[PDB]
Figure: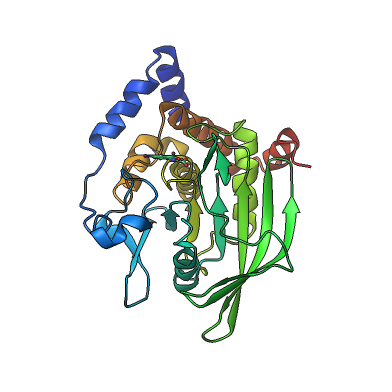
Length: 297
Ligand SMILES: O=C(O)C(=O)Nc1ccc(I)cc1C(=O)O
């Protein structure tokens, strides 16, 4: 039980040390393409790069690079694409990747503006009449509708491949109250949002992998995915005591660096998994309790 491990860590005030231990054990793989000179302007942050082995390749001939990684969780049987907040020059590449990878959902965990800076480009239309067209990747993107709640918004988007006029619906789940280098307001609010994503069908294996991003695609995005995958794991076996959260985080950091950026985000990951376990283990009524606690209307 992770609840015994939690109270133990807490009692001894040792989150920072557990977390430094993860940082020390985590995988180091090359990111040579990330670092090619040509790719300088495709990366938001110097120190955050996809590993070559798990990077997503764009299906184009000029330059196939995007700062994005495939997190493939074999045991759990869920994949995610984690990526940085698109740059003003990489929005067509971002949509190219959603198209090629056949993703149904985009989970955005940041605002465009955070801590006085622009953390991400405005890569989707904010209104129905004003579509976006990405001339470089030959894609149009239209806002079809939005559902604005208190701390998150769900949008439906239409993505058209202008080369073919094939058309797809993309759901965008936008968490707007999760601070950079911070944590959600509560396990309930986080879990309510996670369950909104899950309910939508976006995480399903009939789709390509969900695209998850924050500003760098590591802190908030790693926290989201850790909690999801830990709950999925518990689900398949109905055996919570068999889930080792630090170990599943280390499995995830094989596919992208720096997943989970603070010790408090780690601590929050345990809280969300311990609470979520209630639902996985048969108490379906918690779901509506989280919705109520979350104050989403
Ligand atoms: O958005 C996030 O949650 C996240 O992980 N962000 C970051 C991670 C690493 C670095 I270098 C910078 C940031 C940042 O946003 O400034």
